[PDB]
Image (cartoon, rainbow, N blue to C red):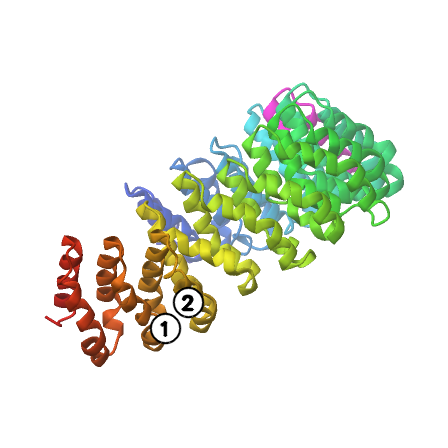
Amino acid sequence: AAADGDDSLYPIAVLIDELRNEDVQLRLNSIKKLSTIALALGVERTRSELLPFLTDTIYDEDEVLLALAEQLGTFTTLVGGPEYVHCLLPPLESLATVEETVVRDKAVESLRAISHEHSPSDLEAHFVPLVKRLAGGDWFTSRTSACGLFSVCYPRVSSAVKAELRQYFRNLCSDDTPMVRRAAASKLGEFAKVLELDNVKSEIIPMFSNLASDEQDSVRLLAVEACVNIAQLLPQEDLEALVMPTLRQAAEDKSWRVRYMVADKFTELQKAVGPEITKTDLVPAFQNLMKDCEAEVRAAASHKVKEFCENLSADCRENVIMSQILPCIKELVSDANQHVKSALASVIMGLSPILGKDNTIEHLLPLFLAQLKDECPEVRLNIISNLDCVNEVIGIRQLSQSLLPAIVELAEDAKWRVRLAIIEYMPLLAGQLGVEFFDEKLNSLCMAWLVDHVYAIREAATSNLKKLVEKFGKEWAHATIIPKVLAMSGDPNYLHRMTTLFCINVLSEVCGQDITTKHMLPTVLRMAGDPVANVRFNVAKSLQKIGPILDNSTLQSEVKPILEKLTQDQDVDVKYFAQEALTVLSLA
């Protein structure tokens, strides 16, 4: 490095320059190239001149520091390799004390990364001292950052040093500052994972317990997670004595936020504790949560209903469900809160395959219908979106026999907001239950909307009919829809006869020239004789709409004559639309 007199610290100068710029987004790119500087500079000078500089001089914005923190996590080689990794601790230590939590986290991430580059000897000589300094810092941000450095260095150090570490983590757990206690509780699980079991059962448990009885709600709530972690590390035999007491204390905590957490992690708690305990403690506890005084907790528990039942031992399963859970589920269907009912409706039918066909029909269908008829759009939408499970269990015929009547009723609601929602369910119904579901009744419903007085409804029905034909095919249309369409041309109810015309207007667009000409046109032409003037002018409008799909020779010999006689009608509107059709079809 002697051959650098004219260099000395040239690259530093280059670096210093760009960092003197005013354009942040550009100074950022500089830090990203930091390595180039390190290269141009030797590893000996990078250590001695670049680092100290990056450790105290830098002042910049938070976005830059972040980039710097990230950079230092990939500088081991660029500084001399494993032999000199600790040289990075100082600048990283500085970044883990900044005010912007996001920057502190990157530094911590980088510190965890290079720790693996330290020889067990360097951990004790350099890494631990750093952890001790941070844990004892005057500024709380330093102590919060320390919490995340314990798990990476504990494994490789001496037994004597491990004992020192356990003690330092204990002190953090009982720090005066809530923010620090919260950070410790959040790392308690991952720290326990690298401890030997003896120390978990003797030291972790009491730290766990103390945090779970903390005076700060925000601290106690974080203990539930630690509870799942600690239970996963212990054998079944130790749970009752080392964990259950605290878990029970959490389930009955005065703060609903703590209880919320228990419900939010009930399935993991279930798996972690095993079926025996699940039966004795969790089953009763679950009933309480479903009946909590706070709706937030009741909603959290509702979401877990199917998963909880699904994981009960096949030994007691159906028994406790029928006798213990079902009754509670019945009451939740009538809960006064919408979030509660929504959460339930998104999972409740997943129970069908667990209860079997007979029970589903017997006990679930009634609840199924109640929710499907709810005032809350979210509730009924969740029911509609999960028909698969029930369908596989009971037949499509049994399901339709139960579902169809309710759909009918909703399809003709007095509120257009509702009628519209039902039209929106059609694609979900077709996609889930298939062609076998669209029977006579269902199809009539889809057609009747075309005569609704609200534009949005007619427009939606139109799209739906076309999508349906596009999915099931024109042959399905020819065999299942047209027959009915034609039958209504007879009906004495004029709205029905009008439905024939509107349907034809839509089907002509997707059934093709052949079916339209052979099975739709004849009916339209015959209706030109209808006694109701209302029907007659729509016949003209309909001929104008489907005419372009027809053969020119058909237009001239069959459409034209009919349109011409309609121009000789006594009704003012009939004569008007007849002549317009003639003009628009160039039969003028």
* Mark found first going from the N terminus, 2 or 1: 2
- From this view, report whether residue 513 is shown above or below residue 155: below
The rendered magenta stretch, by its main secondary structure, is classed as: helix
Q: Determine if the magenta segment contains residue 531.
A: no
Tell me the element at label 1: helix
Q: Is residue 369 visible?
A: yes
| Place of residue 422 in the rendered image (x, y in percent of width and height, measured from the top left) | 46, 48
Q: Amino acid at mark 1?
A: His
Q: Amino acid at mark 2?
A: Ile
Out of 270 and 328, give the one closest to the viewer.
328
Residue topped by disc 1: 519
Q: Is residue 150 left or right of residue 478?
A: right
Q: Is residue 536 left or right of residue 307?
A: left
Residue at the spot 72% in from the left edge and 33% down from the top edge:
328
Residue at the spot 52% in from the left edge and 32% down from the top edge:
97
Residue at the spot 32% in from the left edge and 56% down from the top edge:
498
Single out the residue that lies furthest toward the left. Answer: 588
Residue topped by disc 2: 482
Q: Is residue 221 visible?
A: no
